[PDB]
Image (tube, rainbow, N blue to C red; front, side):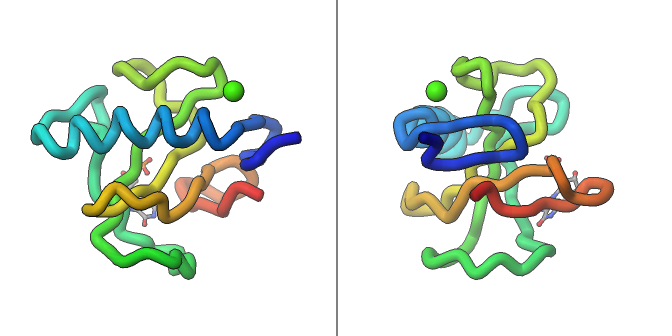
Length: 104
Ligand SMILES: Nc1nc2c(ncn2[C@@H]2O[C@H](CO)[C@@H](O)[C@H]2OP(=O)(O)O)c(=O)[nH]1
Ligand SMILES: [Ca+2]
């Protein structure tokens, strides 16, 4: 069973903490990867009710199981805060345009 289901992509807790740890490290060191400069601030335009406080940062999580290193980011993202607390896992899949919906 999936801990997080983003469209047709299946993720376990370990997939999420692994992706999150990589994004937080880059955030700490003030470095980015890719053309969209990840990790970057997640403004929460959609207004999700995250249990942890802002600011939020997004980092792509890949269905391949690999840690994002620069190519296409896919549609899924892990959202973490300043204290490296997981806010949630989101996706562009099933959302119009460049909007997001939470992964179930
Ligand atoms: N939909 C959405 N995009 C955001 C938000 N915060 C930052 N973004 C970024 O704002 C632009 C318009 O959506 C995109 O560059 C998107 O990039 P990502 O694809 O990297 O999320 C947010 O809260 N919602
Ligand atoms: Ca996996």
